[PDB]
Protein backbone atom coordinates (compact mmCIF):
# COMPACT_ATOMS: atom_id res chain seq x y z
CA UNK A 1 0.00 0.00 0.00
CA UNK A 2 0.86 3.71 -0.16
CA UNK A 3 2.04 3.59 -3.79
CA UNK A 4 -0.39 4.09 -6.67
CA UNK A 5 0.07 4.42 -10.44
CA UNK A 6 -2.50 6.07 -12.70
CA UNK A 7 -2.37 5.20 -16.39
CA UNK A 8 -4.43 7.71 -18.38
CA UNK A 9 -5.32 7.19 -22.04
CA UNK A 10 -6.85 10.48 -23.21
CA UNK A 11 -5.40 13.32 -25.30
CA UNK A 12 -7.50 16.22 -24.02
CA UNK A 13 -7.07 17.84 -20.60
CA UNK A 14 -10.59 19.27 -20.88
CA UNK A 15 -12.12 15.79 -20.95
CA UNK A 16 -13.92 14.03 -18.11
CA UNK A 17 -11.26 11.33 -18.22
CA UNK A 18 -8.63 13.90 -17.31
CA UNK A 19 -11.00 15.28 -14.68
CA UNK A 20 -11.42 11.77 -13.26
CA UNK A 21 -7.65 11.27 -13.30
CA UNK A 22 -7.04 14.48 -11.36
CA UNK A 23 -9.78 13.61 -8.87
CA UNK A 24 -8.18 10.22 -8.17
CA UNK A 25 -4.72 11.69 -7.60
CA UNK A 26 -6.10 14.24 -5.15
CA UNK A 27 -8.09 11.72 -3.09
CA UNK A 28 -5.20 9.25 -2.88
CA UNK A 29 -2.74 12.00 -1.95
CA UNK A 30 -5.08 13.31 0.74
CA UNK A 31 -4.94 9.82 2.24
CA UNK A 32 -1.16 9.66 2.13
CA UNK A 33 -0.72 7.77 -1.13
CA UNK A 34 2.33 8.17 -3.34
CA UNK A 35 0.82 8.86 -6.77
CA UNK A 36 2.90 8.20 -9.89
CA UNK A 37 1.40 8.87 -13.31
CA UNK A 38 1.58 7.61 -16.87
CA UNK A 39 -0.18 10.06 -19.18
CA UNK A 40 0.45 8.06 -22.36
CA UNK A 41 -0.54 10.90 -24.69
CA UNK A 42 1.50 13.52 -22.83
CA UNK A 43 4.55 11.25 -22.83
CA UNK A 44 4.09 10.71 -26.57
CA UNK A 45 4.26 7.00 -25.75
CA UNK A 46 5.06 4.63 -28.61
CA UNK A 47 2.44 1.82 -28.76
CA UNK A 48 3.96 -0.21 -31.61
CA UNK A 49 6.10 -3.22 -30.66
CA UNK A 50 9.19 -3.76 -32.81
CA UNK A 51 12.79 -4.95 -32.97
CA UNK A 52 13.62 -1.43 -31.75
CA UNK A 53 12.29 -2.34 -28.32
CA UNK A 54 15.51 -4.33 -28.06
CA UNK A 55 18.56 -2.09 -27.56
CA UNK A 56 21.28 -4.54 -28.53
CA UNK A 57 22.13 -7.61 -30.59
CA UNK A 58 19.31 -10.00 -31.52
CA UNK A 59 19.68 -13.74 -30.94
CA UNK A 60 18.17 -14.34 -34.38
CA UNK A 61 18.16 -11.19 -36.58
CA UNK A 62 17.18 -13.34 -39.57
CA UNK A 63 14.07 -14.77 -37.89
CA UNK A 64 12.97 -12.16 -35.36
CA UNK A 65 10.49 -13.41 -32.75
CA UNK A 66 9.33 -10.71 -30.33
CA UNK A 67 8.26 -13.02 -27.48
CA UNK A 68 11.65 -14.75 -27.40
CA UNK A 69 13.70 -11.64 -28.16
CA UNK A 70 11.87 -9.41 -25.67
CA UNK A 71 12.32 -11.96 -22.88
CA UNK A 72 16.06 -12.32 -23.47
CA UNK A 73 16.39 -8.55 -23.70
CA UNK A 74 14.59 -8.25 -20.37
CA UNK A 75 16.85 -10.88 -18.81
CA UNK A 76 20.05 -9.17 -20.00
CA UNK A 77 18.72 -5.65 -19.46
CA UNK A 78 18.67 -4.69 -23.14
CA UNK A 79 15.15 -3.26 -23.27
CA UNK A 80 14.33 0.16 -24.69
CA UNK A 81 14.74 2.87 -21.99
CA UNK A 82 11.10 3.95 -22.30
CA UNK A 83 9.84 0.41 -21.67
CA UNK A 84 12.08 -0.07 -18.63
CA UNK A 85 10.80 3.19 -17.14
CA UNK A 86 7.18 2.05 -17.19
CA UNK A 87 8.15 -1.32 -15.74
CA UNK A 88 9.87 0.44 -12.86
CA UNK A 89 6.63 2.25 -12.02
CA UNK A 90 4.65 -1.01 -11.94
CA UNK A 91 7.13 -2.77 -9.68
CA UNK A 92 6.80 -0.01 -7.09
CA UNK A 93 3.02 0.41 -7.47
CA UNK A 94 0.63 -1.33 -5.08
CA UNK A 95 -2.53 -0.12 -6.81
CA UNK A 96 -2.85 0.47 -10.55
CA UNK A 97 -5.68 2.59 -11.94
CA UNK A 98 -6.54 2.54 -15.64
CA UNK A 99 -8.47 5.63 -16.70
CA UNK A 100 -9.74 5.57 -20.28
CA UNK A 101 -12.80 6.01 -22.52
CA UNK A 102 -14.40 2.89 -24.02
CA UNK A 103 -13.22 2.75 -27.63
CA UNK A 104 -14.71 0.25 -30.07
CA UNK A 105 -15.80 -2.07 -27.28
CA UNK A 106 -12.26 -2.11 -25.98
CA UNK A 107 -9.16 -0.27 -24.79
CA UNK A 108 -7.65 2.65 -26.77
CA UNK A 109 -4.90 1.66 -29.24
CA UNK A 110 -2.29 3.62 -27.27
CA UNK A 111 -3.14 1.75 -24.06
CA UNK A 112 -3.24 -1.61 -25.83
CA UNK A 113 0.25 -0.92 -27.15
CA UNK A 114 1.28 -0.10 -23.59
CA UNK A 115 0.33 -3.60 -22.43
CA UNK A 116 2.06 -5.14 -25.43
CA UNK A 117 5.37 -3.36 -24.83
CA UNK A 118 5.50 -3.16 -21.03
CA UNK A 119 4.11 -6.58 -20.09
CA UNK A 120 7.15 -8.62 -21.10
CA UNK A 121 7.52 -12.31 -20.33
CA UNK A 122 9.29 -13.19 -17.09
CA UNK A 123 8.41 -9.71 -15.86
CA UNK A 124 4.62 -9.55 -16.06
CA UNK A 125 3.90 -13.25 -16.57
CA UNK A 126 5.13 -16.83 -16.88
CA UNK A 127 3.56 -20.01 -18.24
CA UNK A 128 4.92 -21.57 -15.05
CA UNK A 129 2.95 -19.21 -12.81
CA UNK A 130 -0.22 -18.14 -14.61
CA UNK A 131 -3.13 -16.07 -13.31
CA UNK A 132 -3.59 -16.06 -9.51
CA UNK A 133 -0.01 -17.33 -9.22
CA UNK A 134 1.38 -14.52 -11.36
CA UNK A 135 4.08 -11.91 -10.48
CA UNK A 136 1.57 -9.12 -9.76
CA UNK A 137 -0.44 -11.31 -7.37
CA UNK A 138 0.31 -8.77 -4.62
CA UNK A 139 -1.07 -5.83 -6.60
CA UNK A 140 -4.59 -4.56 -7.25
CA UNK A 141 -5.85 -3.09 -10.51
CA UNK A 142 -9.03 -1.13 -11.24
CA UNK A 143 -10.54 -0.01 -14.53
CA UNK A 144 -12.25 3.37 -14.68
CA UNK A 145 -14.22 3.58 -17.91
CA UNK A 146 -16.41 6.19 -19.58
CA UNK A 147 -18.77 5.52 -22.48
CA UNK A 148 -20.91 7.30 -25.02
CA UNK A 149 -23.74 4.78 -24.90
CA UNK A 150 -26.11 4.34 -21.96
CA UNK A 151 -26.07 1.52 -19.43
CA UNK A 152 -29.30 0.05 -20.80
CA UNK A 153 -27.47 -0.51 -24.10
CA UNK A 154 -24.96 -2.70 -22.27
CA UNK A 155 -27.53 -4.68 -20.29
CA UNK A 156 -28.48 -8.31 -20.93
CA UNK A 157 -31.24 -7.08 -23.24
CA UNK A 158 -29.31 -4.09 -24.57
CA UNK A 159 -28.56 -3.81 -28.28
CA UNK A 160 -24.81 -4.06 -27.58
CA UNK A 161 -25.04 -6.97 -25.16
CA UNK A 162 -23.67 -7.81 -21.71
CA UNK A 163 -20.81 -5.53 -20.63
CA UNK A 164 -19.47 -8.42 -18.58
CA UNK A 165 -18.40 -10.16 -21.80
CA UNK A 166 -16.63 -7.02 -23.06
CA UNK A 167 -14.69 -6.53 -19.81
CA UNK A 168 -13.68 -10.20 -19.67
CA UNK A 169 -10.75 -10.13 -22.15
CA UNK A 170 -9.18 -7.18 -20.31
CA UNK A 171 -9.81 -7.95 -16.64
CA UNK A 172 -9.01 -11.64 -17.04
CA UNK A 173 -6.74 -12.17 -20.03
CA UNK A 174 -4.55 -9.16 -19.34
CA UNK A 175 -4.81 -8.05 -15.72
CA UNK A 176 -5.53 -11.27 -13.83
CA UNK A 177 -3.39 -13.36 -16.18
CA UNK A 178 -0.43 -11.46 -14.73
CA UNK A 179 -1.60 -12.08 -11.17
CA UNK A 180 -3.33 -8.75 -10.60
CA UNK A 181 -6.22 -8.61 -8.12
CA UNK A 182 -8.93 -7.00 -10.25
CA UNK A 183 -11.41 -4.85 -8.32
CA UNK A 184 -14.87 -3.78 -9.46
CA UNK A 185 -14.71 -1.56 -12.57
CA UNK A 186 -15.78 2.06 -12.21
CA UNK A 187 -18.23 2.44 -15.10
CA UNK A 188 -19.50 5.83 -16.25
CA UNK A 189 -22.16 5.54 -18.96
CA UNK A 190 -23.26 8.24 -21.41
CA UNK A 191 -21.05 10.86 -19.77
CA UNK A 192 -21.74 13.14 -22.73
CA UNK A 193 -25.42 13.25 -21.80
CA UNK A 194 -25.20 13.64 -18.02
CA UNK A 195 -26.03 17.05 -16.46
CA UNK A 196 -23.26 19.12 -14.87
CA UNK A 197 -24.49 18.65 -11.30
CA UNK A 198 -24.54 14.89 -11.89
CA UNK A 199 -21.01 14.99 -13.28
CA UNK A 200 -19.89 16.64 -10.04
CA UNK A 201 -21.37 13.80 -7.99
CA UNK A 202 -19.68 11.19 -10.17
CA UNK A 203 -16.32 12.78 -9.39
CA UNK A 204 -17.21 13.07 -5.70
CA UNK A 205 -18.32 9.45 -5.67
CA UNK A 206 -15.08 8.41 -7.36
CA UNK A 207 -13.01 10.21 -4.71
CA UNK A 208 -15.10 8.69 -1.92
CA UNK A 209 -14.50 5.16 -3.19
CA UNK A 210 -10.75 5.65 -3.57
CA UNK A 211 -10.72 6.31 0.17
CA UNK A 212 -11.09 2.58 0.89
CA UNK A 213 -10.33 0.64 -2.36
CA UNK A 214 -7.56 -1.25 -0.72
CA UNK A 215 -10.18 -2.78 1.58
CA UNK A 216 -12.47 -3.83 -1.28
CA UNK A 217 -13.02 -7.43 -2.37
CA UNK A 218 -11.75 -8.40 -5.84
CA UNK A 219 -13.78 -9.97 -8.65
CA UNK A 220 -14.10 -13.77 -8.88
CA UNK A 221 -11.99 -15.77 -11.32
CA UNK A 222 -11.73 -19.56 -11.58
CA UNK A 223 -8.67 -20.57 -9.50
CA UNK A 224 -5.79 -22.14 -11.40
CA UNK A 225 -5.93 -25.03 -8.93
CA UNK A 226 -9.04 -26.34 -10.72
CA UNK A 227 -6.99 -27.01 -13.86
CA UNK A 228 -4.28 -29.48 -14.87
CA UNK A 229 -1.34 -27.17 -15.56
CA UNK A 230 0.80 -28.92 -18.19
CA UNK A 231 0.30 -29.79 -21.85
CA UNK A 232 0.33 -33.53 -21.19
CA UNK A 233 -3.15 -32.68 -19.91
CA UNK A 234 -3.74 -29.58 -22.03
CA UNK A 235 -4.25 -27.03 -19.25
CA UNK A 236 -7.80 -28.30 -18.85
CA UNK A 237 -10.13 -28.44 -15.85
CA UNK A 238 -9.28 -31.23 -13.42
CA UNK A 239 -11.41 -34.31 -14.08
CA UNK A 240 -12.57 -34.29 -10.45
CA UNK A 241 -13.68 -30.66 -10.73
CA UNK A 242 -15.49 -31.35 -14.01
CA UNK A 243 -17.72 -34.07 -12.54
CA UNK A 244 -18.50 -32.05 -9.42
CA UNK A 245 -19.70 -29.19 -11.64
CA UNK A 246 -22.17 -31.18 -13.76
CA UNK A 247 -24.84 -30.73 -11.08
CA UNK A 248 -24.56 -26.94 -11.07
CA UNK A 249 -26.88 -24.33 -12.59
CA UNK A 250 -24.30 -21.62 -13.32
CA UNK A 251 -20.78 -21.62 -14.70
CA UNK A 252 -17.69 -20.33 -12.90
CA UNK A 253 -17.28 -17.04 -14.78
CA UNK A 254 -17.91 -15.29 -18.10
CA UNK A 255 -15.17 -17.22 -19.90
CA UNK A 256 -15.73 -20.39 -17.88
CA UNK A 257 -19.49 -20.49 -18.38
CA UNK A 258 -18.95 -24.19 -19.11
CA UNK A 259 -22.02 -24.06 -21.34
CA UNK A 260 -24.35 -23.13 -18.49
CA UNK A 261 -25.70 -19.78 -17.30
CA UNK A 262 -23.18 -17.02 -16.61
CA UNK A 263 -23.09 -15.67 -13.04
CA UNK A 264 -24.68 -12.22 -13.34
CA UNK A 265 -22.27 -9.28 -13.18
CA UNK A 266 -19.32 -11.63 -12.70
CA UNK A 267 -17.03 -8.99 -14.21
CA UNK A 268 -18.85 -6.04 -12.67
CA UNK A 269 -19.69 -7.12 -9.12
CA UNK A 270 -17.52 -8.83 -6.51
CA UNK A 271 -18.27 -11.77 -4.21
CA UNK A 272 -19.44 -15.29 -5.02
C1 LIG B 1 -12.70 5.92 -31.87
C2 LIG B 1 -13.80 5.97 -30.83
C3 LIG B 1 -14.44 4.80 -30.47
C4 LIG B 1 -15.48 4.80 -29.50
N1 LIG B 1 -16.07 3.58 -29.21
C5 LIG B 1 -17.05 3.54 -28.29
C6 LIG B 1 -17.68 2.27 -27.97
O1 LIG B 1 -17.37 1.22 -28.48
N2 LIG B 1 -18.69 2.28 -27.02
C7 LIG B 1 -19.10 3.49 -26.38
O2 LIG B 1 -19.97 3.39 -25.58
N3 LIG B 1 -18.53 4.67 -26.66
C8 LIG B 1 -17.52 4.75 -27.59
N4 LIG B 1 -16.94 5.96 -27.88
C9 LIG B 1 -17.39 7.21 -27.19
C10 LIG B 1 -16.45 7.56 -25.98
O3 LIG B 1 -16.50 6.47 -25.07
C11 LIG B 1 -16.95 8.85 -25.32
O4 LIG B 1 -16.90 9.90 -26.27
C12 LIG B 1 -16.06 9.24 -24.13
O5 LIG B 1 -16.07 8.19 -23.12
C13 LIG B 1 -16.58 10.54 -23.53
O6 LIG B 1 -15.64 10.95 -22.30
P1 LIG B 1 -14.54 11.99 -22.47
O7 LIG B 1 -13.47 11.49 -21.46
O8 LIG B 1 -14.08 12.14 -23.77
O9 LIG B 1 -15.06 13.31 -22.10
P2 LIG B 1 -15.85 14.51 -22.79
O10 LIG B 1 -16.16 14.30 -24.08
O11 LIG B 1 -15.27 15.80 -22.36
O12 LIG B 1 -17.18 14.60 -22.04
C14 LIG B 1 -17.28 14.79 -20.59
C15 LIG B 1 -18.30 15.94 -20.35
O13 LIG B 1 -17.99 16.46 -19.02
C16 LIG B 1 -17.58 17.87 -19.15
N5 LIG B 1 -16.52 17.97 -18.14
C17 LIG B 1 -15.16 17.91 -18.36
N6 LIG B 1 -14.45 18.02 -17.24
C18 LIG B 1 -15.38 18.16 -16.24
C19 LIG B 1 -15.24 18.33 -14.78
N7 LIG B 1 -14.09 18.37 -14.15
N8 LIG B 1 -16.44 18.44 -14.09
C20 LIG B 1 -17.66 18.40 -14.71
N9 LIG B 1 -17.88 18.25 -16.04
C21 LIG B 1 -16.70 18.13 -16.77
C22 LIG B 1 -17.17 18.02 -20.60
O14 LIG B 1 -17.28 19.35 -21.00
C23 LIG B 1 -18.24 17.17 -21.27
O15 LIG B 1 -19.47 17.79 -21.56
C24 LIG B 1 -15.87 6.04 -28.87
C25 LIG B 1 -15.21 7.25 -29.23
C26 LIG B 1 -14.18 7.24 -30.19
C27 LIG B 1 -13.50 8.54 -30.55
Image: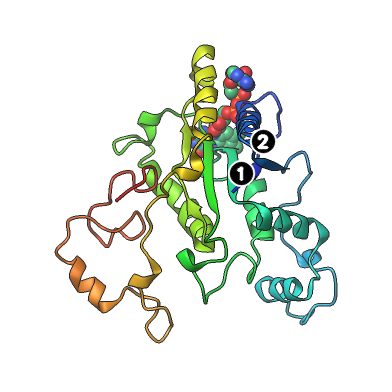
In this picture, residue 125 sits left or right of residue 262:
right
Which residue position is annotated with label 1?
A: 108
> Where residue 28 sits: x, y (%)?
61, 35
**Residue 63 rendering spot, x and y as whole percentages:** 73, 79
Q: Position of residue 7 (x, y in %)?
A: 65, 43
Question: Residue 157's quadrant in the figure?
Answer: top left
Asked which secondary structure carries label 1, the reply is loop
| Residue position for label 2 | 10
Q: Residues within 10 Å of mark 2 (few under 14, many from 20)?
A: many
- Is residue 271 left or right of 134 when viewed as pictured? left
Residue 139 position, x and y percent, is: 55, 55
Ligand 1 resides in the quarter of the picture at: top right
**Marks 1 and 2: CB-CB under 8 Å?**
yes
Horizontally, residue 184 falls left or right of residue 118, namely: left
Q: Residue 221 is drawn in which quadrant? A: bottom left
Asked if 114 appears above or below 193 in the picture, the reply is below
Camera-nearest residue between 261 and 185: 185
Q: CA distance from mark 1 to mark 2?
A: 9 Å
Element carrying mark 2: loop
Mark 1 or mark 2, whichever is nearer to me: 2
Q: Is residue 26 above or below residue 54?
A: above
**Label 1: how many Cα within 10 Å (few below 14, some 14–19, many 20+):** some
Residue name at image x 60 percent, y 34 percent: 31
> For this view, does 115 lie left or right of residue 77?
left
Query: Mark 1 CB in 8 Å range of ligand 1?
Result: yes
Disc tally is: 2
**Counting residues from the N terminus, which is met first, the one under dot 1 or under dot 2?**
2
In the depicted structure, whether residue 149 falls above or below residue 262: above
Amino acid sequence: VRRALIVLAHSERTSFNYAMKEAAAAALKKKGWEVVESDLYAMNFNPIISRKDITGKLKDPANFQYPAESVLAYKEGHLSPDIVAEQKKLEAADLVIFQFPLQWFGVPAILKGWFERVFIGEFAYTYAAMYDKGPFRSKKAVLSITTGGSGSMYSLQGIHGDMNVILWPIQSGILHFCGFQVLEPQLTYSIGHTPADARIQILEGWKKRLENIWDETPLYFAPSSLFDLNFQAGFLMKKEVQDEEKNKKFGLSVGHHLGKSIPTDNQIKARK
